[PDB]
Image (spheres, rainbow, N blue to C red):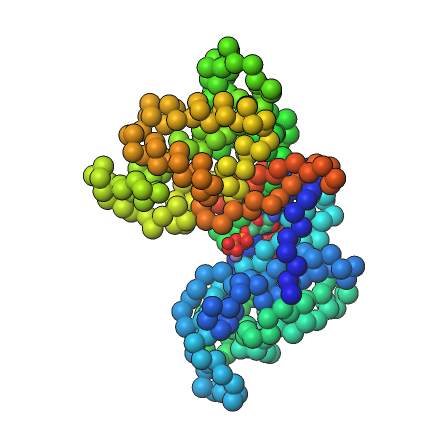
Length: 355
Ligand SMILES: Nc1ncnc2c1ncn2[C@@H]1O[C@H](COP(=O)(O)OP(=O)(O)O)[C@@H](O)[C@H]1O
Ligand SMILES: [Mn+2]
C-alpha cells in the first residue's frame, strides 16, 4: 500500500506534481490513482507514481499478445506526486528532484527493453532510490501506448506539466511574516484592503483577537468574492444559483473545471470553513456576520446567498480538499491551509526537477 501523505510539519511545507512526457500507464478501468512509490534507501517516501489524464482505452498490441486479460483497461499519463517536506529543508527538496530525474532515466530504459510491461520493484544502481509497486496490474508503454515499439523517447518533464502546493499556518495568512506568506498574499484574488476594512466595521466590538479576526475575514471574504466572480464569468451552478437566471451561458463544467482552477492562479486546496476553528466562537460569529454585506454590495441577492451558504456548510473551492494538514507543535497542532500554484512561479522553480 502507498503511504498517505504525512499531515504535520513544524513550519511551511511544500509538495510538487510533475506530469511525465513520452509514455503512458495502462491499468484496469476504475483502478486507484496510485500504482507505486519511490523511497530513499533509508526508507523515506519521496513521491508517488500515479495515473493522471485519461488518454483513451488501452489496446494490447497484437504482436505483444501474452494470454493476459487487458479487458476495459484505460491508458493515462503518468504524474509523479511528491510526499510533502519542509519548505526550508534543502536535502529533502533536492532528493525528491534527483529521485524524479533518476526515475525518468529508468523509464527511458523500461520502454526500450520492457515496452508494455509493468514496472518492477527495484533499487537504483547507486543504491539511493527504491521503487515499491502497490498495484502490479499496470503496464508502462512508450508514447501513447498504441505501438508495440517505442520511437526511442527519452522520458522528460517540462514546466507546463508541473505544479507546486504550499502549506502554511492558517493564522499566518495576512501577516506577510515570511517570503512564502508574501508569495501567497500576492494571489490576484486576495484583497489585503479587507483587513483594515474589517477593523473599521468592528470598533465597538470587544474581540478576543482583532488582528486574527481581520486576517480571517479578509481571507474568507476574498475567497467568497472570487467564487461569485468566477460563477458569473464561467456560468457555474453553485448550490441553488442558476447562471441562466441571470442571462449567463455556462462555459465551464463546474468549480473543478481546469480552466476555473487556472483562473484562481494560486488555488486554495483546503475547505474554507475550517479556518473558523482558529478563532474563538465569539470572534468567528463576528467575522461570519460581516461577510454577507460584502457579497450583497457587489453581487445579486441569489448569488450572494448561494455563495455564502455553500462555504458555510463546508463547501470546497475546487473538489476534495486537503483538510487534515497541520503545522507547529506536534503536541498542540495548528491548522495548515494549502494552495496549489497552477503554474510554478519563478520563486518556486528551484523545487522542481529539470530534464
Ligand atoms: N501538508 C502538505 N503541505 C504541502 N503540500 C502538501 C501537503 N499535503 C499534500 N501536499 C501536496 O498536495 C499535492 C496533492 O494533489 P493530488 O493528490 O495529486 O490531487 P488528485 O489526486 O485529486 O489528482 C502534492 O503535491 C502533495 O505533496
Ligand atoms: Mn493525481
